[PDB]
Length: 158
Ligand SMILES: CC1=C(/C=C/C(C)=C/C=C/C(C)=C/C=C/C=C(C)/C=C/C=C(C)/C=C/C2=C(C)C(=O)CCC2(C)C)C(C)(C)CCC1=O
Image (cartoon, rainbow, N blue to C red; front, top):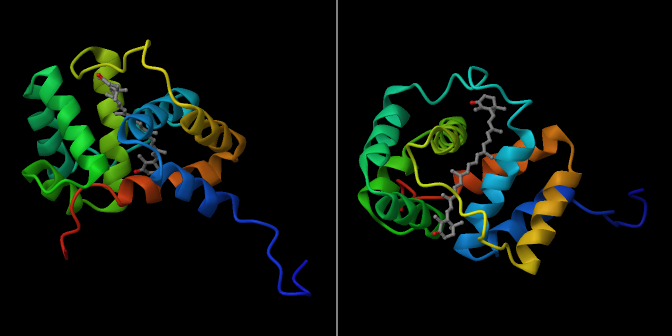
């Protein structure tokens, strides 16, 4: 094991790194396909963290935009563009950020938020990241997803 100073490998840390190197479009698609692959285990009431005053208002703000505006908002989050939505997002706690993305997906399933085109093709790199995440256990999956969405938006101490 650790007797020559070697590390076998950090599956969680490495998945986070390759995810964050993806294009913005691949990031959003991979997040969506992660939701479809764990949406059963995680239950719509098992969240208990998107009905807080902070997240609820941002979700309703996005819900009212046009589909084109909604997509631009999520691209801006992933790209860390300094906009009001990105600033509001960045003051959410990390679990609230996770619950926020989960509720966006539920709103897409319900038809209130722009859907993922099923003819959007994830790139080779994106497919490799999706496969890596699907090969992690459910607990490592939570850890990766939390870090990846935690870094989105604008840092309030930026
Ligand atoms: C339109 C369009 C597109 C659209 C792309 C789009 C619209 C993409 C949208 C993607 C979205 C909104 C994905 C959401 C994913 C949510 C996940 C993985 C949530 C996991 C939650 C977890 C693990 C939470 C767990 C829990 C919670 C909640 C707690 O708080 C407590 C416990 C725990 C922490 C475990 C493209 C960009 C694709 C192409 C161009 C184009 O036109």
